[PDB]
Each structure stands twice: as structure tokens, then as C-alpha cells.
Image: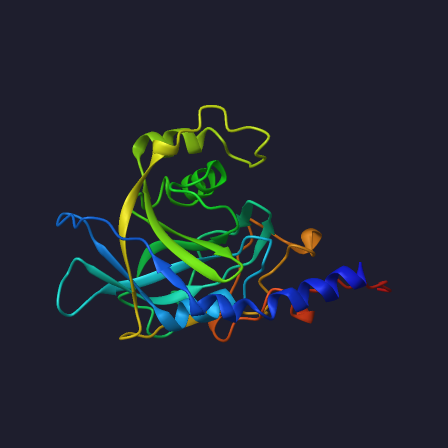
Length: 249
């Protein structure tokens, strides 16, 4: 619907106001665990480009800080082609950004995403998505979950347990008419800090578009996509609107 598209784009124009009230998860320090540090500028943009209803996700990359090897500063957010849902998101593969400058020395740290339900653990869909991405690759990757609701955003970071990965691998394609054997205790608290004392940037798809929610037939979940440094488009940018052509070859 043209009218619904117009209304939904307007609804997102107020998302910047949620950055006026930011809540970050905190717990007793554990010296054996890493501390993950998110630049405020990345959070601001990430929220600005998100949706009030449909989940939006991206990969986080970074490296150790100067003061301490166990402080991981997030340098770059990689927005990859995805197809979002209420309560879940289909994310394309861990991206190849090796051909880009200043990517040497960057570690894959995990993923970041928005959600519209307040929880104290990774949801069933979160667990499945996380396992699909990281189970055979890098199990120490974190999940930064952002509860986005009128007036505010709340940030919590999680690790997935081996039990969590085990169960996630048994649920390969998502449809939450499911969740048999799901346990809220599959995830543990990871240590997160928000900081305006550091700044970060974005890597985006070579063709700019990342939101395939309304272009499902063109989405290639197992696609080999190309990437570049850039400014990410907002969810209801007109470039994300489906268009049709009649072909004569």
C-alpha cells in the first residue's frame, strides 16, 4: 500500500528523540570478561536508520584499546543486506571487507540489532540467528540487543552458551510457531559501555540498499555481496521501495 508506506516512513522521523533517554545494562565487574565499548555516534545513526516495528541488524567490528587489551572498542558497523520481520531478521553472511582500506587489524566482535519486546535474555529467534552466524566461525561473538520503544532505547549485551549454540543449530530456518526446548538461560550477560569519547564509521553494500523487507524476490541470503565505506540509508528510503520492470531482450 502506498498510503501505509507513507505513514510508516513518517513514524520513523521521530526515532532521533529516543536518543534523549539511553539506558545501558550494568552488572558487577568480572575481570576475566572483555568490556565492549560502543561509540555514541554509531548508536545515534543506527537508531536513526531503524524502524519502529521491524527489526534491523548489523555486524560489529573492532579491536583492543590502548589502556587495556580486554577493552574492545567497536570501530565499524557493517550494515548487510537483510530481510526484517516483527520479532526476527534474516541476515546475509558474515561480510568480506578485506579489500577495503583500514580493515586490517579489525576483529569480528558480533552483531547489533533492535527489538520491540523487553527481555532479560536472547529470544528464541535471536539464539537461532546468532548460532547460524557464529557457531562454526567464532563462538565468543556477542549480541548487542536494543529495546526500542516510544521515548527511549535500552542496550544489553549477551554471550550464547554451548547449550545455546547446540539448540540453535537444531533450528535452522526461523518461524517462531516453535520454540520447543528454548531456554532463557541459554544466554549470559556480557559487559557493555556507551562512550562519546570514541567515534566509529559504517560499511554499507556496494549498491547502497540494505533493506530487502519489501524486495524479497531480489534478496539473496547466501549472496556474495560487495561492500564500501559510506552513509547508510534509512529503512523507508525510496531506494528500498519495490519497483517492477517489463523486459525485452
